[PDB]
Image (cartoon, rainbow over all chains, first blue to last red; front, top):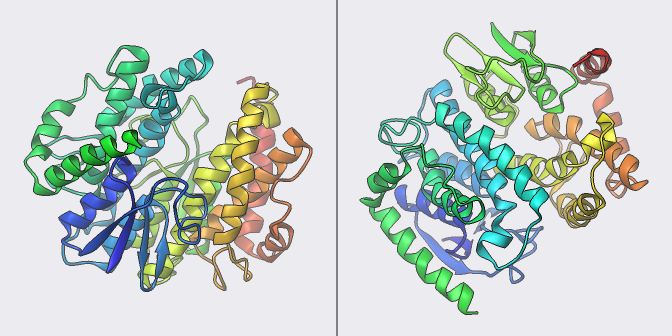
Length: 211
Length: 213
């Protein structure tokens, strides 16, 4: 049985969890806090990581690509190369330009730290460019990349709420406000995978901050 | 035939170019400078981007995945999912943790700007953790992910030299010094693809820097 390692307070962990659940791949969840990870499976100590009989993988999108390839029964990518491209493009744009941009701010927004005004100013200029660019790509019809649920949704379902929260705190504005995110999440809310992931997330987040 | 858009001074452009060359896929290069891109194709103005009859794609790894699916004749990924995964893991680690980390220094290293001491310190602490982590994934036997040329080499071939140059300029030491990068580039040096890419890279860098923009 494949082991998904990390913690449900992690959005990238939840991205993989969503894929696993949607595809009906059996898996075991392993609680591995930062600093308590398997450095042979995850050499830079990042979560999530996956351990199987055949090996380990330590980057969430790499994992999800592996799942697509290893478990073809319920595909989460379109068959057509271009269409699959458009899904991947939405994921990448999302993670590289929205999530990672916002992530520079998380120490302050979420973990009681401080980030400089210079950093804040930098990230805002990026987000101001990147959000409208992402809106150009996203479909929300009703799913992020179109009329079906894909790997892009696995990513959007977990990243969008965090980018929103983060920006509201730092900038006093939800920089995703002009996107149909509330309606998107409502669409997702109905899904059992999403319900489990969100319930687990809240539980782990409480646990993590109790510590 | 597909258009590869951007400019050859770009490492991410060249990553795609190498894949195209290696796979014998025909393409046309379209010059598109930063600030002058086709934003219907590339909404955040990033290069490289690809335009085909069927549509457009604007991220390099997204493009290279597309080429593998659309042009399967000369594969740059193994068939085994786990093996294909190790290759992707190398690309991802390298880009997210080595390239993007060093990229924060490029303004000063390459473009005559200044980055703050705080930024230099930050990035150095990151690279000092991430380089040895990368070294654990990398095989260099003789290729980056193993004994065959893969998509990971298209990435490593372009990103590793830039990370070394950057760090030497900024820190007065090659932070990749403990990896066999010299030997790796020599391995790659013989490849016609790499030779064309490097030639064009240099020509375009000079042109780029000549511009009043």
